[PDB]
Structure formats: structure tokens, C-alpha cells
Image (tube, rainbow, N blue to C red; front, top):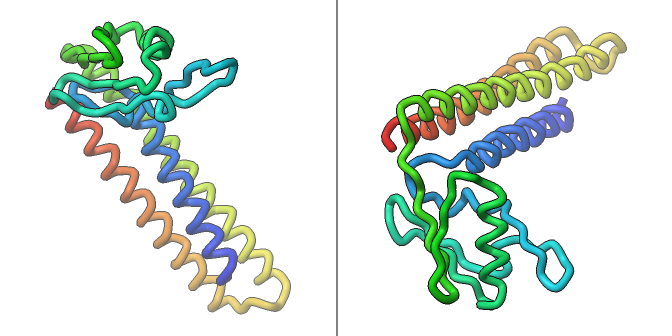
Amino acid sequence: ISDIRKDAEVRMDKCVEAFKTQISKIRTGRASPSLLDGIVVEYYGTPTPLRQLASVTVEDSRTLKINVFDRSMSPAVEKAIMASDLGLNPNSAGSDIRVPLPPLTEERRKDLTKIVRGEAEQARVAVRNVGRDANDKVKALLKDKEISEDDDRRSQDDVQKLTDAAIKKIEAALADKEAELMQF
């Protein structure tokens, strides 16, 4: 009911956000600083996130810029970026690292579009499964006595709404990602 529903909404939300996070790891044709969010570099023997040693910004619509705090940490940062994508050929001068985004081919756009559409369906299925389990919990209460057949039917509706609402956020994120792929 109340708790169950909220629990379902919070869980569905976690899935929607999980979809957007994995969608941001896909490199497109436009400079997107959020793509290097997962980069990690060994700092004094400790695995450290990129954001803690440098600053990723946009200098061009097709080029990224990574300013490393510790200049000595430049080679490692540039190496950690190359080891994560064979398509990235950066260029450093001092504490800066220029990272141009290679324009996608029509075949790559298609290939990348399929992958995003696949993660979306998986994200959509996760949201339904979250709703399905919330319903199974309510059905259990109805099987007892606490809940009437009216409460249960209402819960199913509310849960159905939560699913459609979350699935909408996934289709919107998907659509946006698709647009970026075909546009550049």
C-alpha cells in the first residue's frame, strides 16, 4: 500500500536513473564531459576518479578539454582515457589534454542506436518487474484480510501509473540520445 507504493516509486526511479547513467557512457559525435565520469587513475597507489585530479570541460562542440591539477598526473590521465576507448586520440601540451570526438559514420550511428534501444528495453523491463513485485505484495495482503478487493484494484492502478510515468522518462532519454547520434 502506502509504503509498498513509495518503495515501488523509489525503486523504479533508481532504474530510470540507472538507464541514463549507462546511456552517458556511450560516446557520440558531440562533446559531452559526462562521458568521462567513470574514468579512474592510479593516484599515489590509490584508484582515484578523474574528477578528483582534473576538470573535464567543453572547448568545442566536437572537442573535450581535461585540465589536470597535478601536471605530473597528466600522462596517467591521458593513458587512462585511451585505455577506455580505442577511438579517442587525445593531445596534451602542459596540464591540458585535448580530446576531440570522432564524427560517427552512418554505420556506427546505426550500431550505437541499436545498443541504446536495447538498454532501454532492459530498463523498461526492470521498471515493470518492480511494479509487478509491488502488486504481488498487495495481492498477498488481499489474500489475507487487511486489504479489500477495492483497495487492491486501486493499488494496481496507482502502480500501473508509476510504471507508465517511469517508462516515459526512459523513452524521453532514449529519444534524446537517438537524436544526438543521428545529428552528429
